[PDB]
Image 1 (spheres, each protein chain N blue to C red):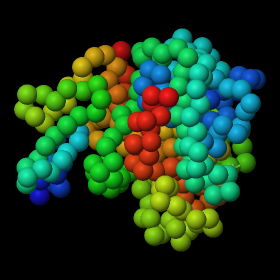
Image 2 (image 1 turned 135 degrees about the vertical axis):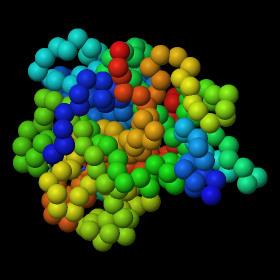
Image 3 (image 1 turned 90 degrees about the vertical axis):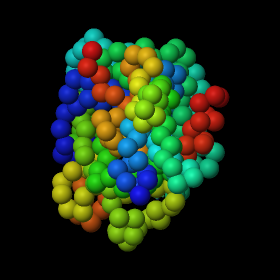
Image 4 (image 1 turned 120 degrees about the vertical axis):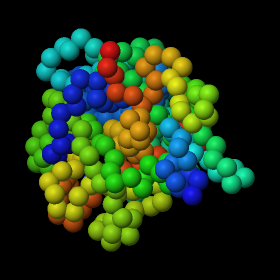
Length: 52
Length: 234
Ligand SMILES: CN(C)Cc1nccn1-c1ccc(NC(=O)c2cc(C(F)(F)F)nn2-c2ccc3onc(N)c3c2)c(F)c1
């Protein structure tokens, strides 16, 4: 079910284009090489509780 | 916040507090970026002059991470009206950038379509603030957070004495004694997805707090994402 099926396996945003899932991230994140995971570009990325 | 628990160290880093001249909070806000705060438009009618404090969890002590910021620009939605509380949204641009650190970090702005299908369909959202802890009591000196269920739109419209427009949504409990309250207005309503929190609403209003058969009414952020994008340039 694409994006309906476990968020299309995306860490964040999921889009259905040509019966294919397309993952994307929030500002401040970089889509990982697998095209699914979102990696923080710098310190204190949005949406993350602070640990340090 | 009625019920719920304290925000522990680093748990609600996106919480902002609008403070008046007497240096006391009267509303909340959400950190969107180093320069922008998201709050309720109706809060701009609660003080002639105000600033924004971030990184605070206890108003009685100096936890060291607190930082007060002067507002450079107030961007209130022109369609807001206190007659209906519709379009209860505003963006504040700070004069100096917020330096992120422990207890000071932004919440993520989601994309509308994804947020409405995935985030707003989750069982719950998280609301937080320094507002009243009971309808007839005082504002808390401690930042609280509360997990609030998304409420069925029909149910909530039936429960309201006032019109729930397309820019509002309900969250909270029918009878359970937990709810946002006076003073939390303008504060964050975020939804957690895979350990990342996205802004989904703005504390707006409610007929009392934690009253039986009443829900907390929030501004539907996903309906203003394009508006927020544009405001974050003014
Ligand atoms: C101004 N008129 C026209 C009434 C109106 N028209 C449309 C909506 N409303 C409307 C109804 C009730 C309220 N009145 C509160 O909003 C309120 C009063 C108090 C108390 F403590 F009683 F003074 N507390 N609130 C409050 C604030 C933020 C909240 O977030 N979630 C909640 N349940 C909640 C509750 C309002 F602020 C606007």
